[PDB]
Length: 84
Image 1 (cartoon, one colour):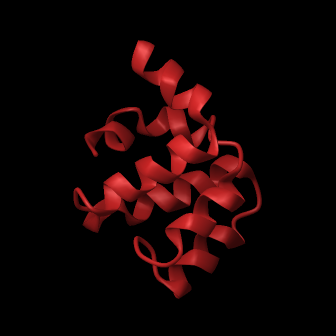
Image 2 (cartoon, one colour):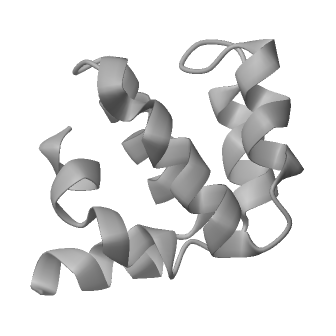
């Protein structure tokens, strides 16, 4: 969803449970080689930013999945992001 795209750089610096947020993206939006690639990054935003690098091929299925996982992980953020 263009939501992750629009409020993109804001997620890079606010998504906290990056680990568990990628756990959900594992089986469908991002491959195995990708899963550990973005997981390799040390810091939270370094990891989060690495993830968005892969968006180049995300469709309403992928960009939506990411959104979905985010909403489950931490709702208060995307809820505050919409009010913005």
